[PDB]
Amino acid sequence: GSHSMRYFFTSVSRPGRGEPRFIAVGYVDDTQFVRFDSDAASQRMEPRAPWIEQEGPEYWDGETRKVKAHSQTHRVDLGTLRGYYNQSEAGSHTVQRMYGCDVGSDWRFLRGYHQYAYDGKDYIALKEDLRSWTAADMAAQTTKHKWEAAHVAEQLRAYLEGTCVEWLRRYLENGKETLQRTDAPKTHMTHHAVSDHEATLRCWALSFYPAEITLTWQRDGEDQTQDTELVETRPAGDGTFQKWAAVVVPSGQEQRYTCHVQHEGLPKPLTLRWE
Amino acid sequence: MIQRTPKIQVYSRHPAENGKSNFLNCYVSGFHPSDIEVDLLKNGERIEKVEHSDLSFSKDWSFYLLYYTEFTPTEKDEYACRVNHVTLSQPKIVKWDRDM
Amino acid sequence: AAGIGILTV
Ligand code: NA
Image (spheres, rainbow over the protein chains, first blue to last red):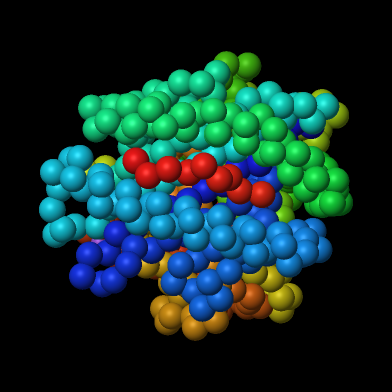
């Protein structure tokens, strides 16, 4: 199947309580593999998947230096952004950055991305061509001018198209057991009366990987999207995911309702029925 | 400033069977800003041995965290997750319902 | 492995 490597960085200011909180995590697909936490004792980039543990001391030293450099940049950013938006110190603010690369089933580069947000909203992002920027407001235009004058996109492009893809392939190979697996969902539906005249029908998918999945309800073949409660896909904690969708239906009409499950691990999409 | 409410789910790793060790999860997703208080409760009391995942976020910038502890379900013991966040005017308790 | 070339805003 297709694959991705992504790094996620969050910095949060806490004025009058010292330095900002900085957390970095890295993922291959839906499997986390590294972390750094600025408040933690180690001050090291740390392994969070078995297959990254074999990387040598140069790797861990080098990744620790990178993540500390990102932390210092974001620390400065929190100050700069307060100035750009004429904000006070009375409150906490959040910078987020995420970047990485996608590859197809043949492990060739599909696309790259490098995005930044301030207080939960898009701030600036590299466009699809990896040569130009989308700035979301006027403050982010200032950053665009500075990043264009400094040729930031060219350095990012070299990473996203090259280095990023090379390390993703390395990780896919070393962690093949975990990363190149598909676990198809184990599916069922549950039925519970909510009164003498209505029932909740809940369609379940369990123990699947990767996390991408579609669960839908139909009534006589007609999608019931406005009437469906669909929960966020959630981790089981063992490396697999769970999700459910529910509808509340008049008792006696169960046989009109079907749940439909799509996942890359299934040989064909499943239709679950009450008959 | 943007604020987004956590979506809270409380559930077991494996289908629950009384007397069989398992994991109790409280997954909170979709929230902003990141500051959040999450506790697992057993019979209304805070469980002390609770781990959590490293802070990460989704494509829309909202945060997610998994809180978890090993547990062995029984008939009588009631489990829940208590969450506070700037979007909630009081802490919110979601009860574990094993018959969903 | 993570990136380098990360500049301040
Ligand atoms: Na609150």
